[PDB]
Length: 165
Ligand SMILES: Cc1ccc(NC(=O)N[C@@H](C)CO)cc1F
Image 1 (cartoon, rainbow, N blue to C red):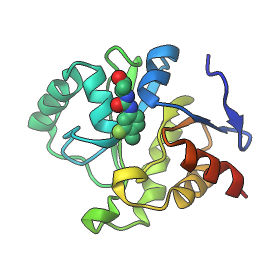
Image 2 (image 1 turned 180 degrees about the horizontal axis):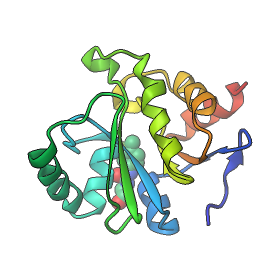
Image 3 (image 1 turned 60 degrees about the horizontal axis):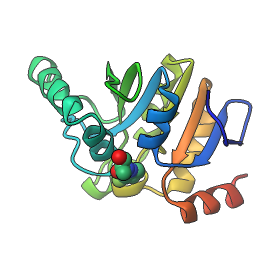
Image 4 (image 1 turned 180 degrees about the vertical axis):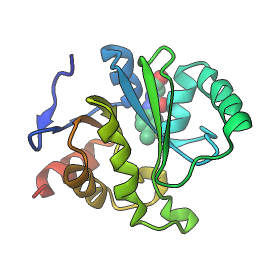
């Protein structure tokens, strides 16, 4: 199971780890992808997860979009986890670098409540432009299921733990 995580609350855990390497190691039931509405996994966590699947995640995602159209900001879809997990929950957090409503971050985290346990990144953090301290606070105040957060950046991980209320 998950190892080396610092317990933040009853159900939220955090670790300074590469989510791709964490997924390959644990093979969780659900790995969360920091997706965009088009499921175009170009950069950040999405680009890294997709590259780990040898682009199989992108091929599956393009078929999903061709059939269903784009996701909503704050929404999600469950697709295969390929070589990383049983499932990948593609969750769209608001991208503040694309001028999207930061109030949609709570709606994005609510998708996690449909899964008993998840390996996840901080939504809207990194290249999505939101304050990761704010993302962690929304995560702890919204998610009720067991979430194991992987934070790639050591310096950000330290800042998140040291500032956690
Ligand atoms: C935000 C973020 C987090 C983790 C990674 N990790 C990654 O690409 N790891 C490779 C070496 C795994 O094969 C990239 C990212 F952009």
